[PDB]
Amino acid sequence: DSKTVLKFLITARERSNRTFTVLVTEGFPNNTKNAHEFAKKLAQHNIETLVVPDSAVFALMSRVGKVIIGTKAVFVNGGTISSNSGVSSVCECAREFRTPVFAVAGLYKLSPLYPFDVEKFVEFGGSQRILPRMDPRKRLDTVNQITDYVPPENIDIYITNVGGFNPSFIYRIAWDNYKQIDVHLDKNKA
Amino acid sequence: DSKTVLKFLITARERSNRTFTVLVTEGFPNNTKNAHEFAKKLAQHNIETLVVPDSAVFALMSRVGKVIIGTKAVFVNGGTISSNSGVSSVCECAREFRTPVFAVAGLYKLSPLYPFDVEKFVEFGGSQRILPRMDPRKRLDTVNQITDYVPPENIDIYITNVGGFNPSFIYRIAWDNYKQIDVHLDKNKA
Amino acid sequence: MSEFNITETYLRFLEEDTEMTMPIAAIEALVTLLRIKTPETAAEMINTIKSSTEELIKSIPNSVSLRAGCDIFMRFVLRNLHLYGDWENCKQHLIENGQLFVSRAKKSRNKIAEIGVDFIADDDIILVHGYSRAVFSLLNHAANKFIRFRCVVTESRPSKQGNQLYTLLEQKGIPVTLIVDSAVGAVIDKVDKVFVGAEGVAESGGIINLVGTYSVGVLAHNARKPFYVVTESHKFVRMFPLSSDDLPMAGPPLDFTRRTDDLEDALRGPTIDYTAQEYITALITDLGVLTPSAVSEELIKMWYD
Amino acid sequence: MSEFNITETYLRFLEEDTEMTMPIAAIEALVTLLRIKTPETAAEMINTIKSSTEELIKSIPNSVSLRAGCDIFMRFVLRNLHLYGDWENCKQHLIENGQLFVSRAKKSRNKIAEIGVDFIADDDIILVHGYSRAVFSLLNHAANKFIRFRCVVTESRPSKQGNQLYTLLEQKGIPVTLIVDSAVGAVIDKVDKVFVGAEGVAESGGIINLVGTYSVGVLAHNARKPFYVVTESHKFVRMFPLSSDDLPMAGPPLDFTRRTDDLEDALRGPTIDYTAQEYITALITDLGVLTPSAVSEELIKMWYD
């Protein structure tokens, strides 16, 4: 669910005529709507693609030595607010194999705020599409999650419109765009 | 300088018809006698081979995800007494990329002794072929080394005639072949 | 007629209150140095403090938080002499600034308690180490907010400070244990967050405070917990190692001289450690929360010239 | 007419000499238990020691080196009752073995000093922690061989033992420093080798001795130094955790009860840590040098049945 790399890997095959493949997993059960949509349009531009399930992504991680992650927002630590589901632990599993971890982000996707609590930005979803039976008498509990967060130690680069950058450099781009007063954006200046 | 993998990768291409390549570095300036001999006979059996220099082996280590090391002897720790030169630090550089590190060893290449000092088994060479000028008046000093030792944490498997084994299991094969008296092989039983 | 060097001004008010700390006490002594002794000329004023700061380093050689105070006071009076007032107003224009830090650096710690609120969250077991008083004022704000947490105090050996912090906040009313510093590695898995405080920040981000903040820092990185550190915006020094070896107290950290009669043997090793950028993950200033790379640049932004 | 339980046999000879240690003192008490009290029947003999070992665990619950001694004495008398002598000779056939360990386990430590020679090599700065007396007898052999090295003693806090070891070998004539346990992380880079000793070995290879041997062990693995440990062949116990939490002394390692009048506050945390196989790299037995995987198998070779 990143329209950047959906558009980018077209011209990454088209102008630069490099041939390769992309493994693609699902954001189960939420980006699997778009995960089947993603590689199909890449099958039109025929970049040797194949869909992996979410459980298999460790077992093929030894082969692949490069991962790109299309994030949603990014904070001052270099810990970014990613897309919907499944992407944090595989970003962790990538980091354990000493594999470089890529990310793309527009300059307007920056945010001058700090991730104080991880859980105040990790938004969840619904009990509907994670099991549809809805038992009222047995009635177990189950957890969805439609936001993943990664630490900046698990990320390596920020492919932006103004260059590639360190995970720790993110303040200097941000404080060239934001000021120390309105980061505490509240009428009570306590 | 391992006649095992010199003979093994013939039939690893011949019977099993797997196609691949091998990078090969030199044991400078000592196994570079045989390093140019090694890939040439593999060029006869044409396994896509290419010779790398010793300095370049970090820069291509990100591509390769499997290394094999033909050792000379092996002790009870799983730290093995390797061949001549250059092989320990690249075994370390392999381990840092979370790359599996292979080794081959015959059962008679086992040794029931312990590596008390690493330096009492690391044998050096000569000042001749590491610089040939032999200045008596400037007269700097220089170091050769014709034995490398690796810890068992940098090794993963022991491809032997009786199976593949842990780096820490090496005692049980050895004590099924050796006894506690003649490991202190000396007339003074002090 | 004072001389402002040792105790004729400085060590007077260090017995006045143990709320002022060591570097701003030197800042309080340095701003009152040129205030009374104002020798009506820009030349010997800075030559007075260059005499006075270098004997103050010579006074106590092993309290290098004072050296950070000796560092930035020169950085204060340099740009304060800038704005180009030809020393005519800059006598008054410095002393009308004057009492800034006894009104502003005294309110470092409550401003730390303004913005250090949302680190100690709901039910965080907190590992503290050493009397870094900005932590306690952050913990003072935590008890005054009635936010829910617990606390764990280590040792501070040989500097004894961990025995104070247990007595300091039990009367405040927080469930707390004092643990030995030896038992960090078997307990840190249950521990979630960890707070320390440096006597000074080095060029890569330095923890130049106590004996084993680097020991508990390298534990927390393998425990993979956010190793926070609490300080303020006047705790910066240029003094920067390459290893974990700073200037020691008097000798190398591996002495092998013998015990003459009854000399102290726990006090043979160092008392100040070092931690680089790798093991911290965030820090607090009066400017705000600060990443360990921005603490390098702000320590270099007005430091190269 | 004795009863062999608490002090009517056992705590007599623990004031005789501080050269015998705790588990073989229990072994000395257990072999003399059935020696005098030999109730001419194989049934109640082992039912006597099952009464006697379980009250001995009940006697001192927090000296689990004794529990290793309580463990392997049953492992001694089991196979000693094996060879199938129908208890006819096996009364005498056990006691003709009898005084084995007061002749053999007493010479554990010199046999450690026979084969632990070629670890402390030429110019090795040695990190020791806690009075594990097999280390000192290895260091006794090192001084008697006149091999060249140095020594560094840590704390043992709160168990105080590091102050003894500094006094114990300075009179022997070794250049040595006592360091605080807080200053390990800033000094360990100069340190090359490190020696400790467990009160008992767990199933994966356990260090169940002191407060922070796991702390100095996890330091040494990031320092990437060979973390050796010195023990002997009678220091094995089945007691085996999954975390670094063993049985504690009396309560959980995070207490939050308060100080009533003047109660001790350093003694709130644990006194025994745990280290798994990952952070050790070699150990010494009377059988020989031993890898941390073989110490698992020999602790399981006669332990499953």
Image (cartoon, coloured by chain):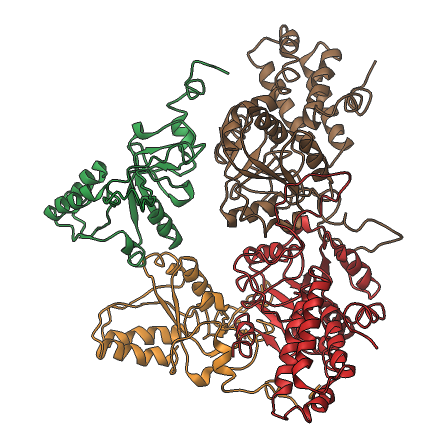
Chain colours: A green, B orange, C brown, D red
Q: Looking at the picture, does residue A190 appear above or below residue C183?
A: above
Q: Residue at x 18, y 38 (%)?
A: A7
Residue C218 is left or right of residue C55, and the answer is left
Residue D138 image-quadrant placement: bottom right
Q: Residue C232's x, y, as percent?
A: 58, 27
Vertical side of B136 occupied by C164: above or below: above
In the figure, C251 relative to B20: above or below? above
Q: Does residue D143 appear left or right of residue C296 in this picture?
A: right
Q: Nearer the viewer, residue A159 or B184?
A: B184
In the depicted structure, whether residue C252 falls above or below residue A188:
below
Across and down, in percent, residue A75 comes to 39, 32
Image quadrant of residue D100? bottom right
Task: Give the side of residue B56 with respect to residue D128, left or right.
Answer: left
**Left-right relation of D197 to B155:** right
Residue toward you, B43 or A39: A39
* Residue A178 % position (x, y): 39, 22
Disc tally is: 0
Please identify the residue farthest to the left as the structure is shown: A44
Give how far across and how far down residue C186 sits, in percent.
59, 52
Q: Name the image quarter holding the N terminus of chain A.
A: top left
To which quarter of the image does residue B21 belong? bottom left
Q: Is residue D189 visible?
A: no
Look at the image and tell me whether residue D27 can be seen: yes
Residue at (42%, 44%) from the top-left corner? Answer: A153
